Image 1 (cartoon, rainbow, N blue to C red):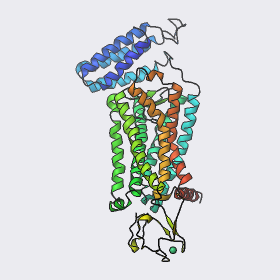
Image 2 (cartoon, helix red, strand yellow):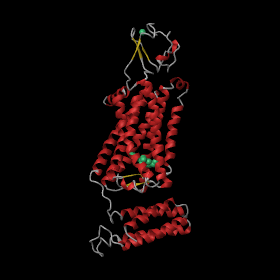
Image 3 (cartoon, rainbow, N blue to C red):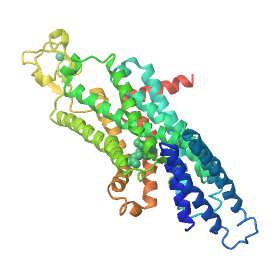
Image 4 (cartoon, rainbow, N blue to C red):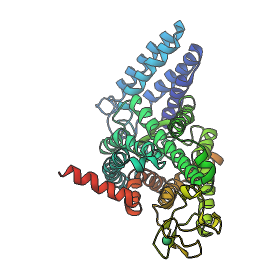
Length: 448
Ligand SMILES: COc1ccc2[nH]c(-c3ccccc3)c(CCNC(C)=O)c2c1
Ligand SMILES: [Zn+2]
């Protein structure tokens, strides 16, 4: 057999022993692993190609396999006895040592010089803005009682979803750039990769639940108010997080969470299972986008048709708000001005609904901050649109599309996706007046 193929063969068997269900499956895979490691010991590596045989260059990697095959021999002793959990454990100890004397053997891959600084600078920016920005968001929702009440409890759920990733995966990835490889165990590999899944998927579905809430608060305002919220919203916030965990469990059976040298981060592999990947691209993207687009489309047509707009009085200045109605005069909160009967008079001066001019301005803060929550979604779709397309190309034709996906393009997609984590609070401050106010209030309180 070859040497590069010998590296690819025993590395494939290393995935089989993991997903194996019995000791005979493990024993069989360790047989194909002992012979492949021995045939690699006969071959000459590319790094010590011009070096001498007795030299600690070619004789250096010779004892590396002696440590390896000996460890396999200890691992198949357990497998022979029937101990599957014991033999699979010793195989992970075979994995940690093998990676420490494999990077010393060959260097096939070639990362373009710009990935290391780009990725790291992006990560540094994102982590710094994510930790500060989404923390202010949490504090402002938790301190402001009127703000939190306006279905903005989902914003906390989303802020933590952004936050968690800045605290565990993002800093580890930055160590993996500076050390040119995964400096942590297989333990921290799949764990960091899993935290990323929760973040990315949890964010889509949180954005989805906000899209539904604002659809039902503007278009079904009457029926909406009939339906409680008190114990409702914490239940859906919990439910969406459990739905996410479930969506992420096939990764442990399909083995799609390993280190990606292209993006220097231990993440989800599109090739590992094209079926699961295809599902991930629908369930965690195409489907929420499809349902969220319907929701904001139905809002924008109502905003276009002049419905759910404020009507300011020409005489005393009283402003009608469809969100509040005029309940003491028999008009319920959620009733549009166009819907109040012609006999209605101003609750402050007494002039009829004939001398009431509408507010032409459709400010972001209006209708529970609908158009700013909209922007948040658009930005999400922009950042995650390329990667999900790359995932879609691979899920369909891996034989023709997968080797035709440029490395330089794949990095650009993960760069955008990583950048999303810090952006959400910035958009709140630029459009939403109340958040901006609260951001200022916190900073002012911190300097006094
Ligand atoms: C469901 O299993 C997981 C598990 C871990 C994952 N981590 C990421 C990800 C994190 C940051 C930036 C971009 C992608 C995805 C999203 C991966 N989506 C695609 C289409 O490849 C992910 C998925
Ligand atoms: Zn008036």
